Amino acid sequence: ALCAFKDPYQQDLGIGESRISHENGTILCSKGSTCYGLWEKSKGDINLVKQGCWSHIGDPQECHYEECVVTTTPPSIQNGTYRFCCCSTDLCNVNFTENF
């Protein structure tokens, strides 16, 4: 999938650089690779932390949510500040939807 991309530490070594548009904020993951997004929230300031490629076909924990949904499961159920989701379709990780 094509995924939303954010990683402030990527530019140093250039990991995945040929697949990233820094201008448009995307990363082309392989076909069969899913996306993730991670946000942190406080009062109620929602900050985007990272976005990018998550799991690939055959990996131990495949993601089969089409949309980026946050459930009452870790990390949120341990610390209410994180919002993590993974999702399988193109650009699905642009934003998150709480499903509590």
Image (tube, rainbow, N blue to C red):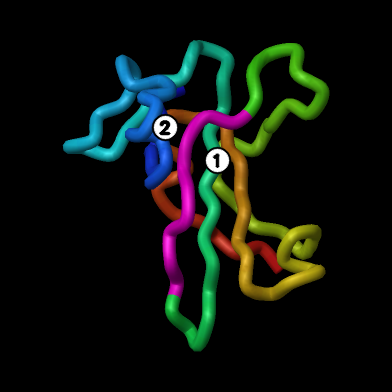
- Chain part drawn in magenta: 46-54
Q: What SS does tag 1 mark?
A: strand
Q: Nearer the viewer, residue 73 or 7?
A: 7
| Residue of label 1 | 36
Instruction: State how far apart marks 1 and 2 are (Cα).
Output: 8 Å
| Left/right of residue 29 with respect to residue 72 in the rendered view | left
Residue drawn at (52%, 47%), measured in percent from left and top? 37
- Is mark 1 in CB contact (under 8 Å) with mark 2? yes
Q: Horizontal and vertical percent for residue 50?
A: 47, 48
- Mark sitting earlier along the chain (1/2): 2
| Left/right of residue 45 with respect to residue 66 in the rendered view | left
Q: Horizontal and vertical percent for residue 83?
A: 60, 61
Q: For the C terminus, which image quadrant?
A: bottom right
Q: What SS does tag 2 mark?
A: strand
Neighbourhood count class around disc 2 (C-alpha, 10 Å): few under 14, some 14–19, many 20 upward:
many
Residue type at mark 1 is Tyr
Please identify the quarter of the rendering in which residue 10 is found.
Answer: top left
